[PDB]
Length: 295
Image 1 (cartoon, rainbow, N blue to C red):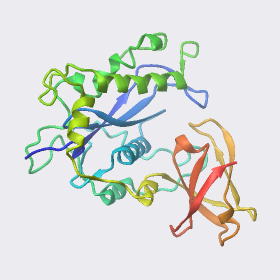
Image 2 (cartoon, rainbow, N blue to C red; image 1 turned 180 degrees about the vertical axis):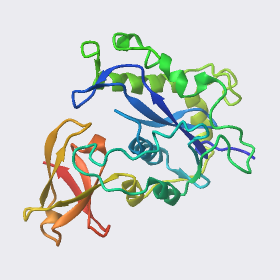
Image 3 (cartoon, rainbow, N blue to C red; image 1 turned 180 degrees about the horizontal axis):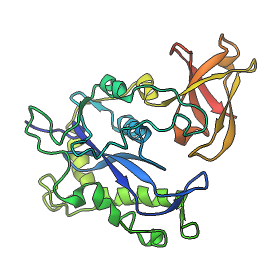
């Protein structure tokens, strides 16, 4: 069969060999999850964190569908043949962000998005080939040249440290630029690129020949993490004591609709990266109420 851009995406992980001082002050080795388009080899999204966990899988996917939309025939692969995604397929401590996070099921969420999940290197019934490229350079490993071995992180690079540790902000900027350069690099030796184009070129060309649908706000919000219900004061404000892997803070959120309505408790959906600005409030039974701004 024929393969469209975005029709089949591969999820892969990467344990970085660089010591980084994270937002909470701890010096750790970051782990990043990447979603890659199988046809063009373009990296479409990622999330990096202190450890391997489902949160990164779930949130990087959200980034991909928000940015490119959802194709009508969508295949997703997380090759756990040799148990390589095992640590990633594990919900972290329920209090990894200090405040407690509600236990839910991401698997259910993907299937609802209209994604056919696969746990092997191939898609049954289609002669599309394999998820991971045979050429290490066309996959996630090819990024070590642009990231882990970038001159700027050389002091913190350990290879396959409180004084050497580089800042989380510098590492994350370097990661984002390495991904950009990996995609834009021309002269790619693949069928689509013919030794001339970059992954970006072929992706832009083929993506324009694909039929995708944009995700609704609700869909996008269902991929956000659910925190255990917090109380709302009479003023329509509630608090989240942020911490764990994130920089400690006692965040207070607000929205008029919260007081001028009926609720005492509310379930908060959030993106760890946006905790500082906007979260989404839901009733204990799941009805969306409104979004709240960090005061």
